[PDB]
Amino acid sequence: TTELKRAFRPLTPHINELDALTILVNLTDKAKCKQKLRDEKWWASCINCVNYRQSHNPKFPDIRSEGVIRTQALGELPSFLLSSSKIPPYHWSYSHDSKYVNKSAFLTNEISCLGKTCKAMAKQLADITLTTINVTLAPNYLTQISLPDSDTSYISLSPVASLSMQSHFHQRLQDENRHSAITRFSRTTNMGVTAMTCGGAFRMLKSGAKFSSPPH
DNA sequence: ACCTGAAAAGCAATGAAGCCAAAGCGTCCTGTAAGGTGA
């Protein structure tokens, strides 16, 4: 049951319609039998996990930060540059508490996502609230950069790590012991689900060989 | 008192480069510190 767990979790590529959703019930465990048990407190708390489903994780270096992001990479940019627009945007994850990292596997495992069944749907559709920025800058832990716009007057920028770029880089760099440079983090369930699967190690992109300067 | 060190042609062919055997076992790879949300 470990290969079924990794296949729905956002650091493996994606994937006869009854075996799946009766496994998706059973990924809140920490089968068809407990798939029948319907707690009204299990249905109303599972809606909280899509409410903190996040596009770009603000908690990525510092797990103390505080904010929710469900937005898309804005605009378009030329060929020699590379951002989270040019890669197809569907690997998203859960950026909230470690209490609900397994209870978020019922409605945020996502090719698209699952975001008295009708009663649940009416509340979810109204508050689904996609394309959401909820950050307050004062009592949290965010980076901040002044950069000039036009002739005068700077703009403050808070870079936030996109999740669809992380799981993209983590998958392609498996076979490369030379262009990959692993950073490990701790208290990883407070980070999010997209950091649980890799175990905390994130497999960055190193600049290949060493540096050697020829005469100029 | 100083100034000079020459040109012209050549640098050979024939044959071979052996094997045979092996590459040891016993035993281990340390522990302590550093949590964000919710009732």
Image (spheres, coloured by chain):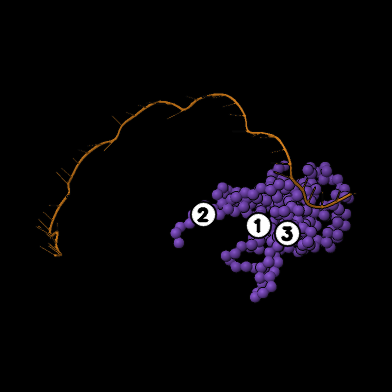
Chain colours: A purple, B orange
Work out how far the residue at label 3 is from the one at label 2, CA to CA, in angstroms.
32 Å
Q: Amino acid at mark 1?
A: Met
Q: Earlier in the sequence, mark 3 or mark 2?
A: 3
Dot label at residue A142: 3
Both marks 3 and 2 on one chain: yes
Work out how far the residue at label 3 is from the one at label 1, CA to CA, in angstroms.
20 Å
Dot label at residue A211: 2
For label 1, the residue is A165
Q: Nearer the viewer, mark 3 or mark 1?
A: 3
Foreground of the two, A104 or A137: A137
Q: Amino acid at mark 2?
A: Phe
Which chain does the numbered disc 2 sit on? A
Q: Is residue A8 visible?
A: no
Both marks 3 and 1 on one chain: yes
Which image quadrant: the N terminus of chain A?
A: top right
Above or below residue A161? Residue B11 is: above
How crowded pointer 1 is (Cα within 10 Å; few <14, some 14-19, many 20+) is rated as: some
Foreground of the two, A8 or A151: A151
